[PDB]
Length: 73
Image (tube, rainbow, N blue to C red):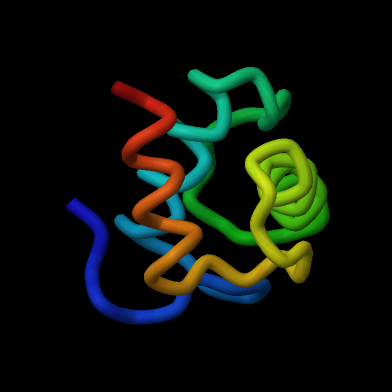
């Protein structure tokens, strides 16, 4: 359900809601799902990238999104 746009710090809206929710389901995102990409989302996403063997950068491009979808199955 992700768009084709890279999700990164400062973003807001539907892609961020889904990103935070998937990271929460996987145990990485602890805060309130608010749809705003700040420190808590950056931290959770980098920890997800590290755990899943992706380059650790805190930006969700195609490969990170695909891994997050696969990991939430």
